[PDB]
Structures are given as C-alpha cells and as structure tokens.
Length: 178
Ligand SMILES: [Zn+2]
Ligand SMILES: [Zn+2]
Ligand SMILES: [Zn+2]
Image 1 (tube, rainbow, N blue to C red):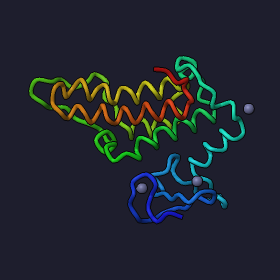
Image 2 (cartoon, helix red, strand yellow):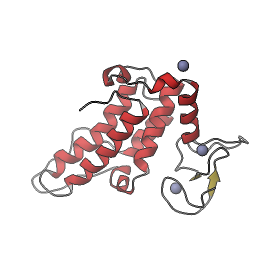
Image 3 (cartoon, protein in one colour):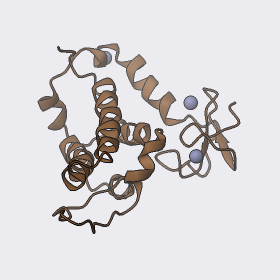
Image 4 (cartoon, rainbow, N blue to C red):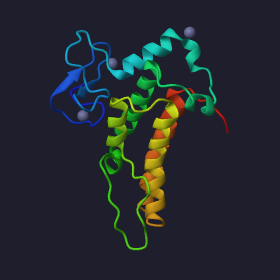
C-alpha cells in the first residue's frame, strides 16, 4: 500500500485498503474509517464496485434528474466520495472550517457554508435528496465569489468549484455536452 494518505498526502496513523493500494487517515476517509471490518474496502473501491455491478450506471444523465434522487445508500456514498474528492485538493483548506467576514466594502453572506459542515450534515443523514448536498457545496463557492468581489483571492473559489463540478459530472455520470 501507499505510505501517505490519499487525501492529505501526509504520513501518520494510516489505514490501508485491502482491495487497492490506497491508504487513509481515519478522519480523512469519508465516511471515517470503520472500527472493525477485515477485509476493508475504501470508498474508491466501493464506488468502482457500484459501476462494475451496473455498467449502465455510466450512461449519461441529466443533472435535473440526478438532483431529485433520494439519498438512498448508493447516492449517500456517491456524495461522500464527491466531498472526499474536493478535500483531496490542497486548496480545500480555505473552505474547510467555519469562515468569518470582516472586510471593508463587503458584507458577509446570509447563509455561511463550509466543507466540515457538509461533512457533518452527511454523517448525520440530514440531506434527503442529492439536491440538498449539491446546493450546500455550490453555496460554499458562490458565497466566496460574492464576498471577495474583485480581489484576486476570488479565484480560489473558481478553482475549487471547478474541482467539485468536474467530479460531480464524473461520479454521477452527467451527459457530456459542449
Ligand atoms: Zn490524511
Ligand atoms: Zn481501495
Ligand atoms: Zn445494471
């Protein structure tokens, strides 16, 4: 197996996947690495299995249909993996913990949002449809863009949003378009 965490790229107390060579810190994996289970399969492996079981699940889909899906176990897992993919980028540090807003010429957002809050919300089964998860994720980046206005720091939101959106289109097999 790898000797660094797949998400944060640091060594430490790592748990190894039994079906691929990836490794994770306990709370870097989503969901948090399960207490027992031998063998253990990581979230990348569990997603691959879903695809292999139902090859047709990779045919193109309309976003509007994806968003209305209820959060049954497979959709819950897909949102966990998509959240994980965002944490995999080092620029996610900017969006992880609860923000605060005190900048001359800007007002803070009405509904602040951050990755660790989405993470908790997923863990607590608070989202009933895919749409709830995707709306909170997009709100993170939209709040950022709106607050930082013309500061070049706004680009960090564009950058991590692009990682989110590309992974959303891949995981949920959104029909390709120009
Ligand atoms: Zn880690
Ligand atoms: Zn694995
Ligand atoms: Zn099938």
